[PDB]
């Protein structure tokens, strides 16, 4: 239908027989693409503009497995463990530059990711229903201690056990990159070929499986990680063994499973599945404590871990990755709510994916027409199924299969709020109903921002602004989107300029004083400055930092805000912007009065930028305040101000930046892209005709230079090293100047 | 003797100001609490100290804290001075609770008591207005302050920049003698 | 050699291997009862056969030779006729130093083999003067002292140097007492 | 020969002669040097590796291999030096190296007399007209230079056990079987000569099954019958623990019948076999389950010799371990009842004990109460102080102890040091013998570095490698081996190492070689790194190994190694005669051969395929078979003209009309 990717000069390497592939990422930037086309390098790309593919050569051979730990930049780099965890943060998150995290894995295939940080999060949604829980009763939190919770300090590492060997993995690196290798060959004997389960209730990691249906022991080795310093003395406590139910089934004994995986919660779920050719038998087992029925067999410690079976399913299937990676609670009687949970997905190597709800396995959609997993709890997948030289596509992501608009939007807002509270990237928009309801969504958002906040919104406003912006993006109201983006950039600019009050000790603080400066005279800011204060505002002689970067920017912004007033009959119901807040305009007035003080101190003030400063910002501030009394609180917009703003002086330039992001409206409509060859069609200025510097690409509009040629403006650079507002998509778009 | 604790929060607010803050205040932390300018053997006798670092909760996807200074042999702390991370409020209370639990563990198992003192450093005027939805602590910054000063006799302190934050007013709840009245224009005092 | 040429040079050196083999002797196990020339290398390689003899049994340095040499007193003459000549100007800490570190590493096993049955016999009573003369050999060789630190790294492998802490401390004390005043403190 | 003798001394009627013909004609084939190599092989063992019964297996393997080479010489060639004078100079070359027989005497203590006796025995059909004179002249050198030597007694008992009885009549001599079992287990050596191993096992199992006969009436008669049946069952269990693979193969090789082989085959094996313990053995014999235990505790009557539920006694042991530890009804009174239950003629008792050891190792194991309980409990230490109707409380007891020691060995290894109730002479020579606190990156030094100078297989390393393969994976196996091989830089050592590498591949040669080719060879000629790797003169013999294993794979050689039988279960399309795996494997090999011959890029892989074509000089070969179905390679032969009589031979694919045409084309 859409989402057309490709490959430029690669192929399936028909001379080479095959190679098992894999890819998985929990947070955003999902794609890893362990695949040798035409071993070869590793790949990285985000869900937005996936055609901007990045890759980097590996440091090993056959590239068995790879997996991340936290949302930050970290990969595994298997095949003797060369190139382990090392964040990038250099220019963007699209360049490996792996550091010396090389684990001393000699001739091994490390396949495991452990040393978990915190406690997980549950989904008590139906018991809460977002009525008045204020996000507390909805997203519960289990209180326990993860492994190696040494020093309340969750040290980070990859102490695990490889696939080739059965001994150990080491080199956990809290600030010191300590190898601390050990030796525990899984009870002094064994061989394995399966993958690992993350963690149990307590701090333990148990996994073993060797051959398949014929030889079916499933051993387990309870372990204790952090005991001593400068060394690891990992344990090897033998745990009860398991098997596959198929061995006693007289139908067929030639199954030989190859997956035998199971979810991260080792409480009651064991999901060993058969992997015959020629068969596909999935099975859910039990992990609970039980007792042996050894009684009444004669004249006449009972608690024994007899891992029995719970349910099974017999069909045909080839490969799969995961069933439901985030996790809900028990006692779930919410059959009416069809949230995407408690499910499973199977992949046909010569075919498509079948998604079925687990624990019933009754029936569901088919999704007709080297394993694929899900993105998050939402129904989002990637098409890495490689029938040869095949790229990735998209299929029906509809988690809610029946038609129920109210319940659909309820699920949508629930998932969005869960994403926001997790501080993760949000991509449930691929499940959106027709964009008209988007308004209602953001409507509920405001309620979630205010009603059931209850006071948390003070620190969540910055994020929720960009959240609702990107929400209304895929909607005919893109003007509202760019208006919200401008609101964001001005709000953060004001919030970074305010703490510059290095005042002498006074009776009160500069923050609350500048805040109360809003309650000031009507006009003539030259009077307001003497009304509040004029002395304690200087902070540096080399104040020449905002003139070439910020002063012209804020001046252009306010001047566009001026000239927007006569543009009432625009091809849009709100035109270009609203100017109905006043609070943001109050921050703008604080900015203009403080830069007036700056000009009084440092002559590198903000000019009118065209001519005839006869300064000229006086009447500007006057009309801003005139609409302010019309836009402070509980007031309507005025006609005299219209006449006052209509005419223009010889000081009115144009060509404002309007920081925004390029669109991606490929729901089911249109997508003009390929696997490569993007076809072409800034805040601190630095937007020339063609870039001639680093020009570190970013999420939406920044694309700012990496060094920035700064002397003391390091506040901005040190502020935007991490993600930005709609600016987590830090790209490495080349300097293909033309 | 030789007992200190550092808690850095003003990353985005005192990025460049941190160099001057170290040159004017962090020097006596080693010059007075040790023989002079610092390679020495590291023991668990109590002569060692700790240092905690916390970032903004907003400019953070999932990670909260990265505290690492059990002993540091009184020199490894000098090693990672410039090894700090950078990122508007800050919500530093979740990081002060880390030092709370750290000194709790110290008093619990590292008790040989050298009355280890603790110092906080901030540039933004932080406040974790939501004191709920946390992991193992549900208190505000004032509750944490009175617990670390009133309940626990650990000497608390906060070294503010030339500006005037709200913690200079929050100092009034420091029941134990903190000696935070005169500012350290001369060499810093062991009790600020 | 270069992949342009065929198997001709390989078969050439093969068919001339017996020529050098006619000049071979044996596996070179050990020949060193000296208490004062043959069996004397320059830098990890004593022999002189200009042809291509067989595998590393003649290429790899005779580490066993050095190990057997350093196990006896008055071994100064061996390394002296080998490499000792105006050591204050020539012996700029060659690799052989790490060799005796391995000997010191073997010292760990001297305290790890049940601590010689908890000093059952004269095992430690001989190892004392053994390590004494071993440290005595250290006269112009403390350069690249991190080798001893690498020995600590070598002590981390297996971590069998626990009981050897007393003996290792003893030998390091002999060393530092021999070089307390004139030596620099940071070294 | 070393590997074959160390792996399967039985079930080798004549595949080994086929592999010998293969390696002979597909190499330099000097018949005198050939028999010299095979003799050095059959005598290099038997002295260094074995210490106990392994030496008996060794001598049995030698005295089975000599008729093998004899019939080889008889059937293989005839018309030029018909294995008469070549054998003369072979035995002369043997007599040249006297330290061989010196070590033989140091090992066997009677190698002079035993050597002469085995020589004159092999002369039953070997040539001795003008040959024994030189042998005597050589042996006269040790005139100065002895209760019973093993070779002579094996040769004597060979026929004595072959035509042992030939008639298992009713009420047969129990004393005969008693004396046979009480003495040394020479029947194992006789079966190792493959003369009756399968037939002996079949007749033995038939006699064992007949000795059940339900129950009996007379007291002493039923007692003797049960004692004989238990002795026979324990002897069969010993035959299984020794080799098993051939025993369990002959158990169900063919026929149409369903006796109680489950208790005879599904008891124990070098595998888990324990997950099915709740499935198959856990029957419901509610009638006389614990009543049998009470009767055994009372009578220590046993006249009911119905030892069919004897294997099903796991059901009674359920409630035994229940009341003992689970229910806690008894501490050692139940232990005393079980001890009375495992009184004389306790054959299946060891089976149930191993089954419950398997159940416990499948259990938590952290408790280890029932584990050590069954260990100290089923111990044959107590030599039946009471009047236990065993009659062999010394020999049968020691054999039962060594049987219980052989099985579940690695199972008890899972726990700490077991009580060691065997107390024999020498334990199992072969074992895991792997450094636990050490990765698998060891074959480079402990194996490859040795065999680099060691011109043999070093049977210890043989079993080490065999265990290492099934504990890992053939892909990384061959990959590591080749990667470590590409550093020799000494063509003599390269040829040595590649020959040994072809050697080790046996018992898995087909699948190993297939995966090796299909995985390395495409990569070995497609990546610049692999180009620079194969750019060495050592790379010349890689294709020599390739063609050597390819023909053996194309040959109808089963090689069904029971050690690797359960592992050989895959599924692959190979990304493609007939639709056979090796067929399309060789087809993809041909395709890669043609592709590497592709122009516009003359890499080291061009020289690689050049050496490959040069090594294609052979007989009865299959390299580029050129079958009339879809065989394209012949066209690529024209491109080989860009590189001659070798062209005339290689173009001779199948003498087809189109084949003749392309041969003429190449002729110009």
Image (cartoon, rainbow, N blue to C red):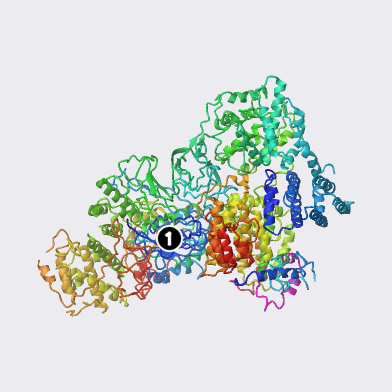
Q: Closer to the camera, D106 or A316?
A: A316
- Where does residue D336 sit, x and y in percent of width and height? 65, 28
Using the image, determine if residue D121 lies above or below residue D645: above
Query: Quadrant where the C terminus of chain D lies?
Result: bottom right
Q: Is residue A606 visible?
A: yes
- Where does residue D422 sit, x and y in percent of width and height? 70, 39
Please check the rendered image and state whether residue C82 is part of the magenta-colored stretch, yes or no: yes
- Where does residue D426 sit, x and y in percent of width and height? 73, 44
In the image, B67: left or right of A532?
Answer: right
Q: Closer to the camera, A229 or A537?
A: A229
Using the image, determine if residue D18 lies above or below residue D179: below
Residue at the far top: name it.
Answer: D217
Q: Chain of mark 1?
A: B
- Where does residue A508 sit, x and y in percent of width and height? 27, 65
Query: Which residue does the numbered mark 1 point to in the structure image?
Result: B118
In the image, A371: left or right of C164?
Answer: left
Quadrant in which residue D300 is drawn: top right
Look at the image and give the residue range highlighted in magenta: C66-94
Please check the rendered image and state whether residue A488 is part of the magenta-colored stretch, yes or no: no
């Amino acid at each position: 239908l859409a989402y057309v990717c490709e490959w430029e000069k690669w192929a399936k390497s028909t001379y080479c027989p095959s190679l098992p592939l894999a890819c998985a990422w929990s947070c955003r930037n999902l794609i890893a693409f362990t695949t040798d086309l035409r071993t070869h390098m590793i790949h990285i790309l985000d869900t937005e503009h996936p055609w901007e593919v990045h890759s980097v050569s590996s440091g090993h051979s056959e590239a068995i497995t790879c997996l991340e730990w936290d949302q930050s930049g970290s990969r595994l780099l298997s095949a003797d463990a060369d190139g382990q965890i090392k964040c990038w943060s250099m220019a963007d998150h699209l360049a490996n530059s792996w550091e010396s995290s090389v684990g001393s894995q000699v001739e091994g295939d490390p396949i495991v990711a452990l040393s978990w940080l915190h406690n997980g999060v549950k989904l008590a949604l139906h018991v809460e229903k977002s009525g008045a829980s204020s996000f507390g009763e909805k997203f519960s939190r289990v209180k326990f201690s993860p492994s190696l919770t040494l020093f309340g300090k969750p040290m980070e590492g990859w102490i695990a056990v490889t696939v080739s060997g059965l001994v150990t993995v080491s080199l956990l690196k809290p600030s010191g990159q300590v190898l601390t290798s050990t030796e525990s060959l899984c009870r002094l004997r064994g061989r394995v070929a399966l993958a690992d389960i993350a963690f149990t209730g307590g701090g333990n990691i148990v996994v073993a499986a060797a051959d398949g249906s014929s030889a079916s022991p499933v051993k387990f080795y309870k372990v204790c990680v952090s005991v001593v310093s400068e060394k690891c003395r990992i344990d090897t406590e033998i745990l009860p063994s398991l098997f596959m139910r198929c061995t006693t089934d007289p139908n067929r004994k030639d199954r030989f499973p190859a997956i035998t995986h199971l979810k991260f919660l080792a409480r009651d779920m064991s999901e060993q599945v058969l992997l015959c050719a020629t068969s596909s038998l999935v099975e859910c087992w039990s992990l609970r404590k039980e007792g042996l029925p050894v009684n009444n067999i004669f004249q006449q410690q009972p608690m024994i871990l007899k891992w029995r079976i719970l349910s099974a399913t017999n069909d045909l299937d080839r490969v799969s990755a995961v069933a439901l990676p985030t996790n809900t609670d028990l006692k779930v009687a919410s059959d009416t709510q069809f949230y995407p949970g408690l499910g499973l997905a199977l992949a046909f190597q010569d075919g498509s994916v079948h998604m079925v709800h687990r624990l019933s396995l009754q029936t569901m959609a088919v999704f007709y027409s080297k394993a694929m997993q899900l993105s998050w709890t939402s129904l989002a997948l990637v098409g890495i199924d490689n029938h040869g030289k095949l790229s990735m596509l998209r299929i029906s992501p509809s988690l809610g299969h029946p038609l129920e608009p109210k319940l659909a939007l309820q699920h949508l807002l629930f998932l969005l709020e869960y994403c926001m509270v997790t501080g993760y990237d949000w991509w449930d928009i691929l499940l959106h109903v027709q964009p008209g309801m988007v308004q209602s969504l953001v409507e509920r958002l405001h309620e979630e921002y205010t009603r059931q906040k209850p006071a948390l919104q003070q620190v969540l406003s910055t994020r929720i602004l960009a959240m609702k912006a990107s929400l209304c993006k895929l909607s005919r109201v893109c003007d509202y989107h760019t208006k919200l983006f401008l609101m964001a950039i001005t709000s953060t600019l004001k919030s970074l300029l305010r703490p510059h009050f290095l005042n002498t000790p006074d009776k009160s603080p500069g923050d609350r004083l500048a805040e109360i400066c809003a309650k000031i005279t009507d006009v003539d800011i030259d009077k307001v400055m003497i009304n509040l204060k004029t002395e304690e505002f200087v902070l540096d002689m080399n104040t020449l930092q905002a003139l070439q970067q910020l002063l012209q920017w804020v001046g252009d912004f306010v001047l566009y805000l001026l000239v927007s007033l006569p543009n009432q009959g625009s091809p849009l119901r709100p035109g270009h912007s609203f100017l109905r807040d006043g609070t943001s305009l109050g921050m703008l007035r604080e900015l203009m009065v403080v830069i007036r003080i700056w000009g009084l101190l440092k002559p590198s003030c903000l000019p009118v930028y065209t001519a005839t400063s006869d300064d000229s910002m006086s009447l500007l501030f006057r009309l801003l305040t005139k609409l302010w009394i019309c836009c402070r609180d509980e007031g309507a917009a005025s006609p005299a101000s219209d006449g006052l703003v209509s005419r223009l002086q010889p000081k009115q330039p144009l060509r404002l930046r309007f920081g925004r992001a390029p669109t991606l409206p490929s729901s089911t409509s249109t997508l003009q892209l390929d696997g490569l060859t993007r076809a072409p069609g800034l805040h601190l200025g630095a937007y020339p005709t063609e870039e001639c510097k680093a020009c570190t690409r970013c999420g939406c509009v920044t694309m700012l230079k990496s060094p920035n040629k700064t002397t003391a403006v390091t506040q901005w650079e040190q502020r935007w090293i991490k993600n930005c507002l709609c600016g987590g998509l830090w790209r490495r778009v080349p300097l293909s100047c033309s | 003797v030789a007992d200190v604790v550092f808690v850095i929060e003003g990353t985005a607010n005192l990025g460049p100001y941190f160099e001057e803050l170290r040159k004017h205040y962090l020097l006596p932390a080693i010059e007075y609490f040790n023989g002079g300018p610092p390679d020495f053997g590291g023991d668990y006798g109590g002569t060692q100290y700790s240092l905690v670092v916390f970032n903004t909760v907003d400019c953070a996807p999932e990670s909260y804290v990265q505290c690492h200074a059990p002993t540091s042999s009184a020199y490894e702390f000098v090693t990672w001075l410039d090894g700090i991370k950078f990122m508007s409020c800050s919500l530093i209370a979740e990081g002060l609770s880390t030092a709370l639990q750290l000194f709790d563990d110290f008093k619990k198992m590292r008790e040989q008591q050298t009355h280890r003192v603790c110092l906080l450093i901030c540039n933004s005027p932080p406040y974790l207005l939501p004191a709920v939805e946390s992991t193992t602590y549900s208190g505000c910054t004032t509750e944490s302050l009175v617990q670390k000063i009133g309940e626990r006799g650990i000497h608390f302190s906060i070294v503010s920049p030339r500006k005037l934050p709200a913690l200079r007013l929050l100092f009034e709840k420091a029941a134990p003698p903190a000696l935070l009245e005169p500012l350290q224009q001369p060499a810093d005092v062991s009790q600020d | 050699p270069h992949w342009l040429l065929g198997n001709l040079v390989s078969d050439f050196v093969d068919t001339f291997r017996p020529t050098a083999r006619i000049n071979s002797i044996c596996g070179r196990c050990s020949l060193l009862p000296v208490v004062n020339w043959k069996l004397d290398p320059a830098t990890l390689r004593f022999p002189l056969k200009g042809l291509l003899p067989y595998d590393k049994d003649l290429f790899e340095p005779q580490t066993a030779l050095l190990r057997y040499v350093l196990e006896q007193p008055y071994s100064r003459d061996m390394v002296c006729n080998m490499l000792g000549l105006n050591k204050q100007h020539k012996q700029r800490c060659p690799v052989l130093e790490d060799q005796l570190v391995d000997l010191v590493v073997y010292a760990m096993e001297r305290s790890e083999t049940e601590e010689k049955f908890d000093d059952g016999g004269t095992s430690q009573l001989l190892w004392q003067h053994l390590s004494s003369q071993l440290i005595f050999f250290v006269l112009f060789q403390f350069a690249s002292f991190p080798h001893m630190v690498l020995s600590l790294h070598q002590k981390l492998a297996g971590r069998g140097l626990i009981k050897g802490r007393d003996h290792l401390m003893w030998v390091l004390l002999q060393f530092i007492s021999g070089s307390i005043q004139k030596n620099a403190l940071a070294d | 020969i070393l590997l074959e003798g160390t792996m399967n001394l039985t079930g080798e009627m004549q595949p080994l002669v086929e592999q010998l013909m293969m390696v002979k004609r597909m190499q330099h084939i000097p018949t005198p040097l050939f028999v010299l190599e095979i003799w050095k092989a059959c005598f290099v063992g038997l002295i260094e590796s074995p210490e106990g019964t392994q030496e008996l297996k060794w001598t049995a393997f030698t005295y089975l291999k000599i008729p093998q080479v004899l019939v080889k010489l008889k059937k293989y060639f005839h018309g030029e030096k018909d294995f008469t004078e070549d054998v003369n100079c072979a035995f002369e070359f043997l007599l040249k190296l006297t330290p061989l027989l010196d070590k033989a005497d140091q090992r066997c203590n009677c190698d002079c007399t035993n050597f002469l006796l085995q020589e004159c025995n092999k002369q039953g059909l070997l040539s001795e007209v003008n040959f024994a004179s030189l042998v005597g002249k050589r042996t006269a050198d040790r005139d100065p230079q002895i209760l019973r030597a093993e070779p002579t007694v094996t040769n004597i008992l060979k026929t004595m056990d072959a035509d042992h009885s030939k008639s298992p009549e009713g009420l047969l001599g129990v004393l005969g079987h008693m004396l046979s079992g009480k003495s040394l287990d020479l029947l194992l050596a006789a079966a190792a000569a493959t003369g009756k191993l399968k037939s002996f096992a079949r007749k033995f199992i038939n006699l064992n099954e007949f000795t059940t006969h339900g129950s009996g009436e007379s007291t002493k008669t039923a007692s003797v019958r049960a004692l004989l049946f238990d002795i026979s069952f324990l002897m069969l269990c010993h035959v299984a623990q020794t080799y098993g693979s051939e025993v369990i193969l002959s158990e169900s090789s063919s026929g149409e019948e369903v006796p109680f082989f489950e208790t005879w085959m599904q008891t124990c094996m070098p595998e888990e076999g324990k997950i099915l313990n709740p499935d198959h053995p856990c029957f419901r014999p509610d009638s006389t389950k614990v009543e049998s235990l009470v009767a055994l505790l009372n009578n220590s009557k046993l006249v009911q010799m119905k030892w069919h539920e004897a294997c099903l006694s796991i059901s009674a042991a359920i409630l035994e371990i229940l009341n003992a530890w689970e229910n806690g009804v008894l501490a050692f009174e139940s232990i005393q009842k079980i001890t009375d239950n495992i009184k004389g003629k306790v054959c299946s008792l060891a089976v149930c004990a191993v089954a419950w050891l398997v159940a416990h190792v499948r259990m938590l194991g952290l408790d280890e109460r029932e584990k050590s309980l069954q260990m100290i409990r089923q111990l044959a230490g107590p030599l039946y102080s009471e009047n236990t109707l065993q009659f062999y409380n010394e020999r049968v007891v020691i054999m039962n102890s060594i049987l219980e020691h052989m099985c579940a060995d690695v199972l008890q290894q899972t726990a700490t040091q077991i009580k060691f109730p065997s107390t024999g002479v020498d334990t199992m020579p072969y074992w895991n013998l792997l450094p636990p606190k050490r990765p698998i990156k060891e074959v480079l030094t402990d194996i490859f570095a040795k065999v680099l100078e060691k011109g043999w297989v070093d049977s210890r390393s043989i079993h080490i490698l065999d265990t290492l393969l099934h504990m890992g994976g053939v892909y990384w196996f061959c990959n590591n081996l080749i990667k470590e091989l590409l550093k020799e830089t000494r063509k003599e050592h390269t040829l040595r190492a590649v020959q040994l590498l072809y050697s080790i591949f046996c018992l898995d040669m087909q699948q190993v070689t297939l995966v090796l080719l299909g995985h390395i060879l495409p990569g070995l000629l497609t990546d610049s790194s692999k180009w620079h790797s194969l750019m060495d003169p050592p790379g010349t013999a890689l294709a020599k190994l390739a063609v050597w294993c390819a023909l053996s794979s194309y040959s109808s050689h089963k090689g069904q190694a029971s050690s690797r039988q359960k592992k050989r279960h895959r599924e692959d399309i190979e990304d493609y005669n007939m639709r056979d795996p090796l067929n399309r494997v060789l087809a993809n090999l041909f395709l890669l051969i043609s592709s590497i011959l592709g122009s516009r890029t003359a890499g080291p892989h061009t020289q690689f395929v050049q050496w490959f074509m040069e090594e294609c000089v052979g007989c009865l070969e299959q390299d580029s078979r050129g079958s009339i179905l879809q065989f394209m390679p012949f066209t690529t032969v024209s491109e080989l003209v860009k590189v001659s009589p070798k062209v005339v031979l290689a173009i001779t694919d199948l003498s087809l009309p189109l084949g003749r045409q392309v041969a003429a084309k190449a002729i110009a």
